Image 1 (cartoon, rainbow, N blue to C red):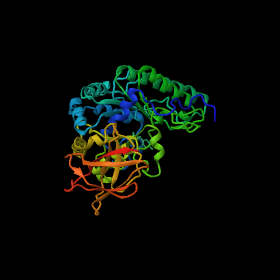
Image 2: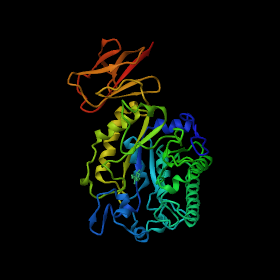
Image 3: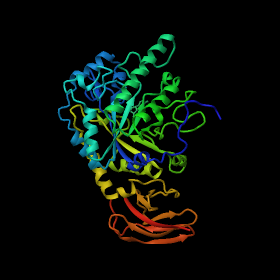
Image 4: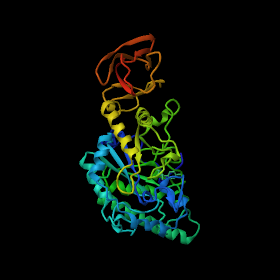
Length: 438
Ligand SMILES: Cc1ccc([C@@H]2N[C@@H](C)[C@@H](O)[C@H]2O)cc1
């Protein structure tokens, strides 16, 4: 036991209603929108292959010159009601929005910096319009916030001098000012998802990360805070020096997921994965031919994979500079929504089922002991193997969409073949099991 002032504050999962809501939502969308959408990964005739939102770094653009992109910020096709409609039709239950990325441009009219939407031709409070429109559709809003800020010359990557320490202290005050402003201007916010907290400067000021968590929790009742914000007294991140999760949920599975056999430890805490459609582009990049682009079924597999292991999944969108979505993203959101409309009873408010993983897909468990089989890989044998935990038996199987009864055959003690449906559903599909405990 290492004594810590700024280590973990929760013991186990939060079970207050706000955390239950964060969890039951399960499926979210991410929006990365900022000045990087304007060049879209290209600078002065070179298209950079790195993530578009990092183009300032790839093209070595000085801050003043990068931030002059504000003069081009005029997304005339933006309509927050249309964005909220697209999210609703996709089946998302919440949206995480970049309030400010590393570049430091704010999507709300901050009084603490001139680098904001207010000082662009468009003028309007994008973040405020989104909060209202998403909330009008019943969709929760979460705020992404980058602590690292390339627009503020008080930022420091490490503290190597008295002057660095004074500057970084001013930087933390500026950061607190913005965070309090977000929390009070948009009091329906349900979560702060911090990024840009990996530098030595933040690791040496773990106390500040704990402070920011506590400050936001006092301002916004029931607010969630991600693990990535948090460093302990020793500079240890996400999990403290005693191995305890800091913040309210683990937020490290970013473009990767826990193994369904080897990583069952994740079922012990809340967690949220986020993923990009291309291999590694969050902000708008004009050239999606540069890396592999996931198909809708690949995305749906990841969504179900997360819920099957007790986690949420957030699918990223990088809107165009004009305020509309690219056709690949409109197609993705539509295809996800069509699937979720049909099969979402096996996703929303579901969790880890405690069954041995099988090759056909994933199990999820509903709030009333329903066990859903979500089938992604159709066996040529036309039999879906179900091995039940000790004392659990399968009483019935039903095809979710039609309610048709599915034959269940016991093959050995604790093992069944559940028949595939008489007609191949032609897409990933759900069979609902009625199970009984000894
Ligand atoms: C190494 C690395 C740094 C920052 C990131 C940022 N976090 C993602 C959620 C995006 O915002 C990406 O810019 C990703 C990888």
